[PDB]
Amino acid sequence: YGRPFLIIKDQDRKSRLMGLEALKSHIMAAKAVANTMRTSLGPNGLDKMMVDKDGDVTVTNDGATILSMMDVDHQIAKLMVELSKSQDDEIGDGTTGVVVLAGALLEEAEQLLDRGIHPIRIADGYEQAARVAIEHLDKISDSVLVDIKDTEPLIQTAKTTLGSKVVNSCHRQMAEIAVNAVLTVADMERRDVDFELIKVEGKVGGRLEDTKLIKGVIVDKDFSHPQMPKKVEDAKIAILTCPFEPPKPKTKHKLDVTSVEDYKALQKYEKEKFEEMIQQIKETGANLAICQWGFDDEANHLLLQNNLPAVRWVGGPEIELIAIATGGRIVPRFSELTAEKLGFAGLVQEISFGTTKDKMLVIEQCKNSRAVTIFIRGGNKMIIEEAKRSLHDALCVIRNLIRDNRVVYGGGAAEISCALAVSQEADKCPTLEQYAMRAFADALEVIPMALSENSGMNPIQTMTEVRARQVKEMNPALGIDCLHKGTNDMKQQHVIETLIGKKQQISLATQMVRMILKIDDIRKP
Amino acid sequence: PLSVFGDRSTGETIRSQNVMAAASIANIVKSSLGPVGLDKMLVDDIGDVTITNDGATILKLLEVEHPAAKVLCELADLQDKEVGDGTTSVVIIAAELLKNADELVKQKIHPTSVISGYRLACKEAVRYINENLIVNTDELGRDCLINAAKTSMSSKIIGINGDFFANMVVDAVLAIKYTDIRGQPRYPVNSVNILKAHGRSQMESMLISGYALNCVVGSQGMPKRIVNAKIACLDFSLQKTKMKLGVQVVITDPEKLDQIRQRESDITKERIQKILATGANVILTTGGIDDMCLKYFVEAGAMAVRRVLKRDLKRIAKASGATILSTLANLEGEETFEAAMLGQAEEVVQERICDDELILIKNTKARTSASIILRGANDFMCDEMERSLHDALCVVKRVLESKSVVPGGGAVEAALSIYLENYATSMGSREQLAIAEFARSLLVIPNTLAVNAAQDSTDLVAKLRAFHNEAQVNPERKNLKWIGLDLSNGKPRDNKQAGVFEPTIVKVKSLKFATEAAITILRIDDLIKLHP
Amino acid sequence: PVILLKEGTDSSQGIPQLVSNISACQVIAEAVRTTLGPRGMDKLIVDGRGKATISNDGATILKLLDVVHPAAKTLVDIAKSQDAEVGDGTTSVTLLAAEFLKQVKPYVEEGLHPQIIIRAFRTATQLAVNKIKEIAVTVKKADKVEQRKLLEKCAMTALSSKLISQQKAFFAKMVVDAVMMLDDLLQLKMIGIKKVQGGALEDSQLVAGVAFKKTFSYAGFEMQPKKYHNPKIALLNVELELKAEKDNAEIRVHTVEDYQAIVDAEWNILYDKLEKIHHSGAKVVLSKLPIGDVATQYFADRDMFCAGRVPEEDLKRTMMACGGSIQTSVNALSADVLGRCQVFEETQIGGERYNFFTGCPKAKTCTFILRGGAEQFMEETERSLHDAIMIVRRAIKNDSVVAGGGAIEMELSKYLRDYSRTIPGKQQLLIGAYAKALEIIPRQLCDNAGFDATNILNKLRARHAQGGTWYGVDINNEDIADNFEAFVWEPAMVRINALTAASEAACLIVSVDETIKNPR
Ligand SMILES: Nc1ncnc2c1ncn2[C@@H]1O[C@H](COP(=O)(O)OP(=O)(O)O)[C@@H](O)[C@H]1O
Ligand SMILES: Nc1ncnc2c1ncn2[C@@H]1O[C@H](COP(=O)(O)OP(=O)(O)O)[C@@H](O)[C@H]1O
Ligand SMILES: Nc1ncnc2c1ncn2[C@@H]1O[C@H](COP(=O)(O)OP(=O)(O)O)[C@@H](O)[C@H]1O
Ligand SMILES: [Mg+2]
Ligand SMILES: [Mg+2]
Ligand SMILES: [Mg+2]
């Protein structure tokens, strides 16, 4: 006698899915995600047009931002988006490949679930195959020289990593700009870089060829007076934080005026303080002062009469950027200024644009600077965003190269070699674990097949030909010719990829597959 | 995936639901098992009250919407239609077997081995039942039928007054025995008239030696007491003659319309005169009789009963040796009536029993009939008494047809459980646990009997098991197997000399039906319900 | 006529109420039934806000179930009690209670007194506790290497059914070194668990000091060197910014002379405070209150580091690692109130700036860096780390491990059966059912592993009756072996506590025959 009671507060409005149905649904969702994020892989892949909620159009090629801007609702899709975000935050390049690898690994595991294999054994075999591939990939790792003199391998790697986005017309120019920015902000004594010193500014107008770097700091302001000189040759930067106002404490103060003498003294001091501060600023012999706040009315006229240009409304990171580039020190008041707290300039000329009233001030020609700015030019906002994303990806790639100081042979040879090594190692493992290694090796070959499908050639035929050519000779560098050059050797085509990045991608994909193969229940309201 | 447009269940969800439904069905009818349990009450939506506790009626009037419970309902209905007694015990046994097999299924055991073990245990129990048999004709005989009828009427409303009811049932069965090929003693039931009339109590419900009719006399001028009368069975309407649809009347001569209208009424008069030419007194008609035809029977001093049922007329013609004549035609072309096919009753007295009257017919000269007029309080008591009488008649018929009796109670089930436990040591395969579960499922009848009696159940069960184990081994104590179960005090007694008597055809059939139901239900693990 | 109780009160009898309670307990236990051995799988709970919760521990699953049943809350209570006590067997006690309830359900339906059942449960629990305390067999005098090996084996056994089971040989030494450096009070609040996105699971490290996330910065954060050889950490708690002295102050300045005097005196006080802070010989300035832009630029001109908005727990951990003290006033900055370290770096991990402090030999705390997933994986790793830390802390204070798997349950069942085979009466059936209910642990393990449970249970029973005591189940060889020789140990405080909790839950559930619910 069991009447239908009530246990959960929302039992009548909740679904339950146990058994292998939840795992099958998760595998299907992962396969659908991998198929959706499949065409955006390789040099022949097209871009994706994203539509925002308010109505903004964003066309990009990076898989990380595409997956992030998709506000879905499934748990597997959210897990894949989080995995792609973590991969982009750790490495920076190859965000659309880890998801494809995870989908290919989860697709091949569906046959073992229907045949009669426990998911724990599948996860153990996948982890063993991933460890074997990681241990084998470090044997074919060639170390290249990286320094300030020879920059050919870095330029080649930056050009190879930037052959799929819309910013491919310059190629050599963007790679040179990136390697120059890296050599400027390198810090070889600690083997790390800082992205807070490299500022990227984008504006409408111009073309992609006019994206020349500027060895200095650029601001988006102008002079406070139109009758001031725009360009100067010999100027001394003087960055200050106190405004051009009379002193006033932040506490509660009240001034009392009794007779006419007090009012006269106050009226005299009102201009005496300004005259004293002007004389103190002029005594240091500076030629270009920089204040944090704005100016009033008498201070600007005094600075114009004394022939001393100044910049208004510049109290952000531009102060520290200029202090790092030129070499000056920030001062708190006006007394401590006549010492060695000034910055040497070289060319401070206010540039112009088209018919609009947009005036920007730039500072170039400096000494041993440790911060450079890149001025992006284009014809559309999406073009500027894509150029900024490509520059960030190139910077991350060069940072990984600096941190690793060694590369391998990418393209379509490393995955095939890893699959061959896994298949060879699986022949000496007779303990039911040979089925997972074969699936792991077959899932790793999804990159050359996708590349050949996106190029326009036969995938399986080219894969078999490359495998035969690699097993016949002793050159593990023959990949898939996506540019139709007639040579399948990736060494002559200067195809350089990262090793630690690929290792981290493989490890993250294996961990995600193991985590997915463990969940089999779902309870949603 | 899988576009079905309907709710489905795969796994342990449908099995648990079926187990819960079977448990609820068993617990619903678990308050009227044995002579200790009381009755039930079923009320509809208009105010009609129905008091019953037979088992099949409770499952029929309950509005069951689940298939797992509908299977048990139709099984109980088939069991009640077959034998007539033991409708709740079979359902309880089937529910206990299902609950015991669910635990084995949930223990990572294939249902095929469990089904095979259950079939083997059922076959062993059937083969062991024929060993413990007592011939009713080898002992006293007359004292066994009374005990069986008292046991069958021990869990009804007439539990105390069962001494006279048993004798009445025995007399009715002895008087209703028919004669056929004279090879096997056949005792057909559903042949007595069970009339329900309020008024007197239960001790004033005597047995009438003859057939009773639930009809009154036609006209008030007809007598109501004719001694040594003749019963005439007719099967045609005794009204005015009317032509068929394909036969019309076209009046072309006014000198013949009056003659035709006079003949249309004189034909019936001539037919009545030819029928009553042999000196008939009791005339039974199934159809309606016109008011003009009753005057002849009134003036002739005879009785004419109309609206008589076909079964009652057939039983009257069979008891009195008459022949129901559907027409007056013979082997020639003239309607003649003979006196060789007429009844011969003793005395027909129309006695008034509580406002309404009824015609009573005593025994004749061909065969002997019987009728039991039960008198209750209101309407539910009469229905309960009729149901108890029918159950007692069915039990007596089954006992007389089986020619054997088995002491019922908590003895046969315990003996079968002990025999199955002693037999599980020989089966060294995977069917060892199935026999144990089958033996443990049979011990649910004494548990329920002790629970309904509000007494100690575990101690009594242990004592019965110890007694059965002591009676099985050692041939010097083979007379301890007839202990039974006495719920009046809570101690074993003698259930063979003067205790509980039950036939052997009820236990075997119920056990086989419960096993078949458990087998046909345990093979279900996928439910698909389409949307209307 | 007026009714007794308010309109909307529900009541029932005893037998149907107990049957409903048993059914609810079975339904609740069936949810956390597949989560037990290493072959078990976790669940995924989604609340109303759309946030997923993936955890293998049964405590979080029972907490996220949101059960409003008045009788099903007994399992959650004992689960929380076990998680707060030893923090390990959260589902074992629930499974044992469900098995006891399912075993006593037929005895209750047959018509038995609940007081006798409660007395039998208490007697069986006392006998099991006595047997466990008798067959404990602990070491009397062992070396430090033996204790370290025992702790490592206990950590590996506790981290065998979690998600980090493939890397159980790496976290064991880490948790051992973390527990060994916790003095004697064993403070759990001094262990910082940081979760940084990026990296792999094997890239986790354990520093011997303190490490926190970089807070807010001004325009003077890039003009200072973030590396020092042997610096000095000065713990402060005063605000270093240009602000008023007191909120309830009023200055009645006369003419311009007093105004200029006050303006100069404010900067003089600021410079005097800065000089008094710098003259302490420190290089790293840490304070809970945010630091202004003036002090950030003043400290950058003398090769000094500063950081504001330091949390209280991070500051306490840094003080416990170094050896300084919280100095609110700057008028007493000596040498015994400053920190000391051997190395100080500032690297970038996962795109986020983090500060590292290590090298001090007198460190009494540490910091964990968990890498892997993004949120759910990191939470699972943190839960597994906390469970391993609790297991090691319990094994340190108990120093008495036993065989895992299912040997202790089989031994307890055999002892209970041997004790019941002597006493007659109705006390034999209850103890027999209690002993048979303890055999569900190996059956559940075999069902979760996908092996034959009947044959394994029969072989284990035969081996226990023919004895050859610490014999459990085996998942690799798909047979039976010695759990004590396979380095499978577990603390004895987990079985006794779970047994007592299950006995208390059974005594509280059985002794209930009425349920009254008030409206609203
Ligand atoms: N010129 C080329 N020759 C060979 N392989 C290439 C070439 N350009 C791109 N690829 C391959 O295409 C894949 C995708 O590269 P791309 O879309 O540019 O960036 P990401 O690797 O981040 O998707 C890379 O793994 C690379 O091996
Ligand atoms: N006088 C009696 N003494 C002992 N047991 C009895 C007695 N009458 C009936 N029983 C037992 O009670 C059980 C239930 O019988 P009953 O309630 O009449 O309906 P059914 O036979 O349809 O279950 C039977 O199995 C019988 O053994
Ligand atoms: N390596 C192992 N060998 C044998 N038994 C194990 C092993 N790891 C775990 N177990 C068993 O699995 C059971 C579950 O333990 P665990 O998952 O750590 O906590 P909980 O008991 O709360 O589920 C334990 O009772 C233990 O005996
Ligand atoms: Mg790329
Ligand atoms: Mg009966
Ligand atoms: Mg645990």
Image (cartoon, grey):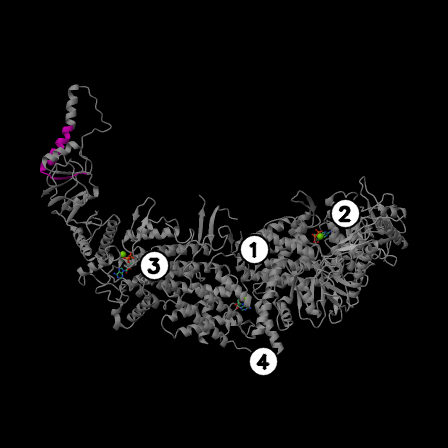
Camera-near label (3 vs 1) is 3
- Disc 4 secondary structure class: loop
Asked which secondary structure carries label 3, the reply is helix
Report the Cα–Cα distance between label 2 and label 1: 47 Å
Q: Are marks 1 and 4 in contact (CB under 8 Å)?
A: no
Label 2 SS: strand
Q: Are marks 3 and 1 in contact (CB under 8 Å)?
A: no
Q: Quadrant of the N terminus of chain A?
A: bottom left
Q: Kindly identify which residue carries mark 4.
A: C141
Specify few, some or many for label 4: CA neighbours under 10 Å numbering under 14, 14-19, or 20 or more: few
Q: Amino acid at mark 4?
A: Lys
Front residue of C46 and A388: C46
Mark drawn on residue A110: 1
Q: Please report whichever mark, 2 or 1, sits nearer to the chain's N-terminal start.
A: 1
Compared to B323, does C338 lie above or below?
below
Gap in angstroms between the C-alphas marked 2 and 3: 85 Å
| Residue drawn at (29%, 70%) of the image | B467
Which one is in front in this view, the residue at disc 4 or the one at disc 3? 4
In this rendering, the label closer to the viewer, 2 or 1 = 2
Q: Nearer the viewer, residue B316 or C288?
A: C288
Please name the predominant secondary structure of the magenta segment in the image.
helix
Using the image, name the chain to which the residue with label 1 belongs: A
Residue, disc 3? B93
Amino acid type, mark 3: Ile
Give the number of marks: 4
Viewer-side residue, B344 vs C343 = C343
